[PDB]
Image (cartoon, rainbow over all chains, first blue to last red; front, side, top):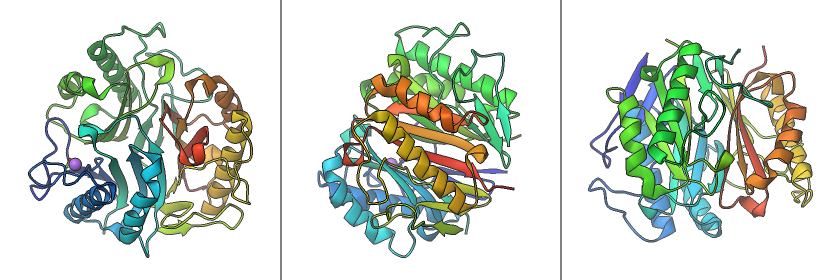
Length: 125
Length: 124
Length: 125
Ligand SMILES: [O][Cl-]
Ligand code: NA
């Protein structure tokens, strides 16, 4: 019915949330932020941050039995709409052949003062 | 498609409903900390968070779901410095069951509240 | 999974599509108030809301869905002071059918538009 996805390959979801759920053949990821497995921000650089988020999401999807080519929808929450071209360049490297639906908005603030946070909805397989 | 609107909460006034149910999935509206009179309960962020989750529990129940069936939660907040206080209350509702979550600080919330939460949940 | 791109609307720039359709559901990209020339139709927030909802009406049709099939709307806005005016336009599109909704004020939207709306919808019949 429902699967709860948590991988020690990734920085822990501390406290009351998990890396992803799988319900009715759909994966719902948590928002990923640019932490490595030690739970440290990888870089001040917004392109380095976007790559770590997308590398994190590739692992979530693998563990949930999905892949990037199965993504229906991404939401990109960012700190600075002026970084959008830089973020979009890196995103386009992960979403080349497959181009899912997307929304990108500038928020006030992200966890740990990170610059980018991305959540996915993906199909199993 | 089933439209959910419970009289156990203040009416969703204007062009929305408490939730919809489609293909065995409940999509809640973003709840804000209105009491049953439709007044903001308090300026206190832990009270607001509790009011929001109490409201969402009633929505899930009237939609044929429950908090243990939640897939995904999105938490929109006014102040990321309140995150630990919000998380404490949140973990009283999602204690054994820990669904997927995103939490961002927005610029401003309806009625200048400090938290709004929406859920995606499985029908039991 | 089906990819939706309509020529009726300004092209998705780079690595996204107008919508995806997967397991009987349409996920739309967030629509901003661009006309078919990809220009911001107007400074007026009610004209912008109208263009957004006209753009989403066409995505839903191309996806094989409609406004009376919508499960969930997310309304991103630049100014909570505009909420009454946006809601007035939105209620014209959602009078017979009232979906679930979330509405939040973001710091900034693409091209400094005042409103952006994404939808999750059921395939029609
Ligand atoms: O939060 Cl991984
Ligand atoms: Na993360």
